Image (cartoon, rainbow, N blue to C red; front, side):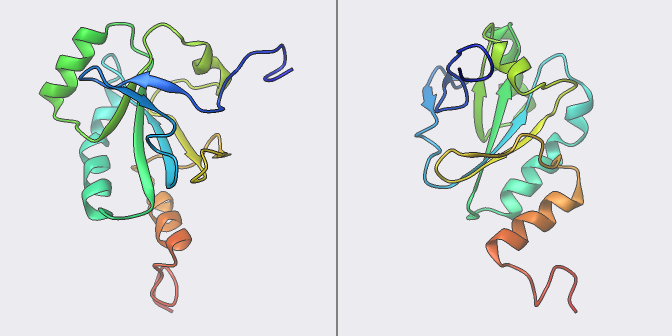
Amino acid sequence: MSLRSGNPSAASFSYPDINGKTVSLADLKGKYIYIDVWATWCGPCRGELPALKELEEKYAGKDIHFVSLSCDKNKKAWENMVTKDQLKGIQLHMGTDRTFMDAYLINGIPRFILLDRDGKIISANMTRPSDPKTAEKFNELLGLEGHHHHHH
């Protein structure tokens, strides 16, 4: 069955947001979803995390949800961390159900994923926020090209 054995995954997930909010795939459904991975023990991500905010606040209004998923087991440590790190946005925390971690072969962090408005996984591997080609994709799919990405 699903995945390979018979496990229910990808088809509408529901995780707790930092504050303790049940955030489902319906909370995001209706607009394109971008799933990036965020972690406490991940330092490299923090190099582009500020730029991820820039991406959000620069594209504020776009048809994309920046959704950070954390495979961190230490919730309280991580929830206070994101409060400290000020990485506010649209965010979810896994914890121990890291079967979904392997389901996407997520490793390193951050992992780049993209899905359709419906919640339909489009790209299991899309484009890192610090990758300029991801921004190009946003403009493109919105038709935000000035004749095209680089004015020609």
